[PDB]
Image 1 (cartoon, protein in one colour):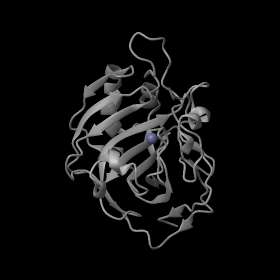
Image 2: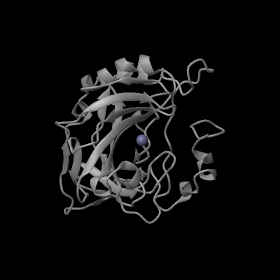
Image 3: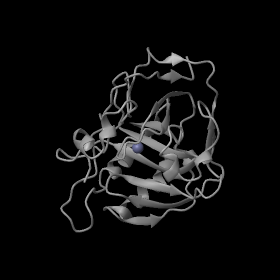
Length: 257
Ligand SMILES: [Zn+2]
């Protein structure tokens, strides 16, 4: 099955998922000088006041913090979007060392990690229908750099010991994803895809300019997770990022100058 290794990683995905070589794949390098400032782009509206986290899951690739998406409680709107997108989960991608881990790059710079908050367009009724549509998902991407600790991350870090291995989950209620946001909501945006299989070309990407800072200790706890299941040979969960893909016939727009 697919993964991040030599034998099943990004360079192999196209064999089971041909859309890997498609026209709107993600992530991409963001060339800051080429990105067009678009004064028509609206401020991002992030309304997470009523977010209901339920559970955290080690799915063998990363960990997902899941939300109750059975009502409009945690939604993304505005920005480049038309209509309302409901938060379903967030997860991260990270490296074996602090010099790699992000999926998007900025002028070829790699950050230590990247957070993806995944939302689906309510006009399609459910996530599985939304991913079949070119405007089905809005993913908010946030870079992580290593420096000061992120206090709002610590609850996530401290549950990871209980989901070390693939297929482990744990109750994870009352977590507030607002604590993972940077000060500014300035962004870049472009049409793309899921960054892991099935690689569906259904995402409006919204990548924030301002990274969050996490501590070295925080990131080191990410790197103690396992890709393998309980009892299986230990393979540390590191380098679970897809590299930048060709931009092809796409324009990256900036909300800011
Ligand atoms: Zn992701």
